[PDB]
Amino acid sequence: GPLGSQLIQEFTAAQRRGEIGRMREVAAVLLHFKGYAHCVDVYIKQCQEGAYMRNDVFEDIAILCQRVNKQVGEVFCSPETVMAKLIQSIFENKIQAHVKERLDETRNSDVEQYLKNLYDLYTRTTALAAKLTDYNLGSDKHTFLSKLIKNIFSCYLESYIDMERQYLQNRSGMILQRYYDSKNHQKRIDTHGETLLSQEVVVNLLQETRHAFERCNKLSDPADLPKNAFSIFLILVEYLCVDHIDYALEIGLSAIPSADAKNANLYFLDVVQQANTIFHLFDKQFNDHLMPLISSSPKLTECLHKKKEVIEQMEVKLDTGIDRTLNCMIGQMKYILTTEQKKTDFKPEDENNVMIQYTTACSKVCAYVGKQVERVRRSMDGKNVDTVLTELGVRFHRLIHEHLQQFSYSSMGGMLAICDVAEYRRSAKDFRVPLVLQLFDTLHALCNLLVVAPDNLKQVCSGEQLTNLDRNLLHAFVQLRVDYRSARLGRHFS
Ligand SMILES: [Br-]
Ligand SMILES: [Br-]
Ligand SMILES: [Br-]
Ligand SMILES: [Br-]
Ligand SMILES: [Br-]
Ligand SMILES: [Br-]
Ligand SMILES: [Br-]
Ligand SMILES: [Br-]
Ligand SMILES: [Br-]
Ligand SMILES: [Br-]
């Protein structure tokens, strides 16, 4: 019939000014007809008009819902259905308008600020939805809020991961270019030991990626959180690893003079030092930040495999470079020995007038060794420096060991050999590595063989420093004696 439902305008008047049960009476009448849905509707519009006048909209709607809750119980019979209508109106209108307002402007002017706003707006909305769930709305309310948040973020959170990666690729690219421009280095003799490894570029790349993970944690669907957080990681290993540090490792690998003369190749040891600190900053953000997001991954086993693979590819290159730098040093110590150690040193031309000291070949080497050891300590941190010295010291002991075996020794030449080793031992003591010192300790005892009289030869072999050594090793040194044939020293087949 002629619905004079425009007594709904009588309800509007009652709400305008004055607190009354007149709102209740008109509402109680209106539930008898279709139009009770419209009455509560205009009630929501009116109480919202004077509300939004604050800098913070999420506090404004929090105060709005509390004052409406105490009033709605006075006016309507089923406050729970009215209340759900309220917050739905707040979300579908006010919240969605405030989100579209913040994002449209910054979307085509500041992509990073867009991501930081989308993250902030989504966080405050969820925190707000947790405040609204405290009210006695119709249970299953949790699903109700979830649909409201989804209906105003579904398309923002859909194209999220693509904008996040497009941003990170571009921002990382700009950081790398800005660094290679400040060094006047176009991609693909340099006297400077330029490592091309910035501890600023890496820490700024990690700064950027860390923040991307945090946004990824809350803005990515939990079912796709692992695959999304790993997509971001692959961007890091493409710019930080492949493009920055792996590039500087190959560039630094070509500045090695290849075991020749005149080598100012302190360069690569500086590269090893920086790369190690970079690695410590790398896996630190990996364990603390990326791992909590990837822990629940279907194929986490393949995620850890690529992380390991990447960090081993460059681990090997560092091991190739430390090896090439070491035999460059061994190459020079060998050069000193061949050109400055003659036969007449251990096989003196005239037995009569010989002053026994360590050879000039010995001092030239020890002086060189010490000059390089110093450069190693000054170019590396305490942890990885002892592993390098150990290798150098082992190779150092190896060189002298085989060097001593290509000479014949007279009675007089014997002492000169010990004097050499004794000085070599002091040079090795400067390594501060027990292994190197102990290796020359056995070589020192070994030289004792080509000095003692033939009758006390098998006696000395029974000594504490020699007994626990292989008989073949004792034999190799006895053969170096000039009177190995002149005496019955062939009794070393036992
Ligand atoms: Br009115
Ligand atoms: Br209703
Ligand atoms: Br952020
Ligand atoms: Br959240
Ligand atoms: Br409930
Ligand atoms: Br930078
Ligand atoms: Br990439
Ligand atoms: Br280091
Ligand atoms: Br980090
Ligand atoms: Br001496």
Image (cartoon, rainbow, N blue to C red):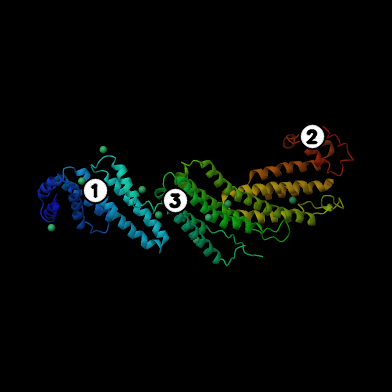
Q: Quadrant of the C terminus?
A: top right
Q: CA distance from mark 1 to mark 2?
A: 106 Å
* Side (left or right) of 299 relative to 193: left
From the viewer's side, name the closer residue of 494 and 286.
286
Which residue is disc 2 drawn over?
A: 459
Type of amino acid at the residue the image marks with label 2: Gln
CB atoms at circles 1 and 2 under 8 Å apart?
Answer: no
Image x and y of residue 15, in percent: 13, 53
Q: CA distance from mark 2 to mark 3?
A: 73 Å
Ligand 2 within 8 Å, label 1 CB: yes
Residue at 60% across, 51% down:
314
Which residue is disc 3 drawn over?
A: 213
Q: Which mark is residue 85?
A: 1
Circle 3 or circle 1, nearest the eye: 1
N-term mark: 2 or 3: 3
* Side (left or right) of 14 relative to 301: left
From the viewer's side, name the closer residue of 395 and 203.
203
Residue 182 in sight in this render: no
Q: Is residue 490 above or below residue 264?
A: above
Q: CA distance from mark 3 to mark 1?
A: 36 Å
N-term mark: 1 or 2: 1
* Side (left or right) of 64 relative to 13: right
Which residue reaches farthest right? 486
Residue 181 in sight in this render: yes
Type of amino acid at the residue the image marks with label 1: Lys
Circle 1 or circle 2, nearest the eye: 1
Type of amino acid at the residue the image marks with label 3: Phe
Ligand 10 within 8 Å, label 2 CB: no
